[PDB]
Length: 55
Ligand SMILES: [Zn+2]
Ligand SMILES: [Zn+2]
Image (cartoon, rainbow, N blue to C red):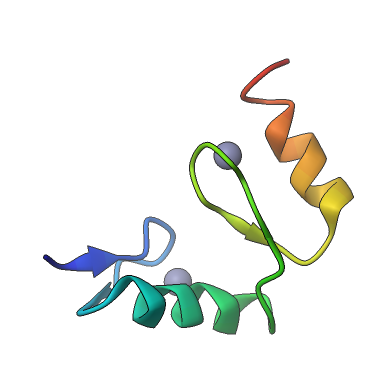
């Protein structure tokens, strides 16, 4: 199933593929939003984004 970037709209074959695509945009992919699966290199950037799901 085409796994595409919600952000830029490129579909990948694998999740890890798109995961590395998502990693590519931020350099590296550390944390993810435990809800929507957005990768943040900063847990605080993440946190603020986590708080929009529970804020
Ligand atoms: Zn992207
Ligand atoms: Zn999120």
